[PDB]
Length: 225
Image 1 (cartoon, one colour):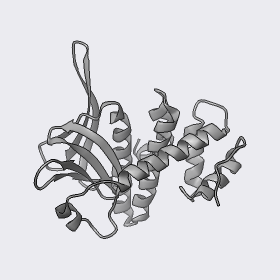
Image 2 (image 1 turned 135 degrees about the horizontal axis):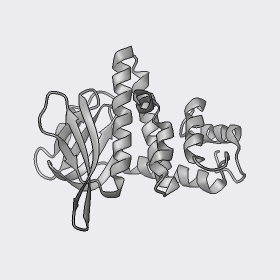
Image 3 (image 1 turned 60 degrees about the horizontal axis):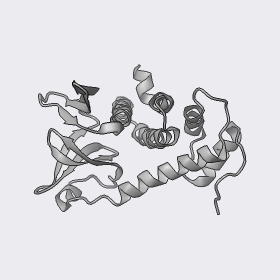
Image 4 (image 1 turned 30 degrees about the horizontal axis):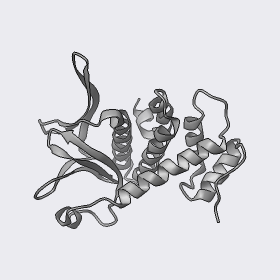
């Protein structure tokens, strides 16, 4: 069936090849993906960029599929709730573990019992801050998430991945705020598609402007802006 494109792609070609790949079908979102991948450059996608985007998406999907969840967590997931993005093991103010993002919420998967912390639901987020702690030559990137009516801020040392997680969390938060305001779950599904595309864009572009380019897909967060 589908084979990776071998010719340069204008926008309309790109839309068709992404649809054929099965990664996403919504042409409007793929248009934003095109804008993200060509940000700053000429408006065309070459085979190498397409191949890198596809590989990054599939790698993130495979990492997420291989997640090890404690049964206690799995018993309290909603129906059809799944991990779509898994971080590396990181230091946090709740212990060392991997951050797992579902459609609904963020978990930390930890050593021991019960083996997880629910960090926050996208509904209950109050503020998300992307910071870096400095001391002499040391720089510690720190993602901060505050939940409504809860004093303790969650802090994660996500290293070079911190900017991406900051963007993905803000977009999933904004998507849920809008889904709740419109009583339309489709916003959550669109936000999830948006953030997984952002992840693949960042992995593809390999640049300091990559988070700015990837924000072309942060449809719901950009609205709040």
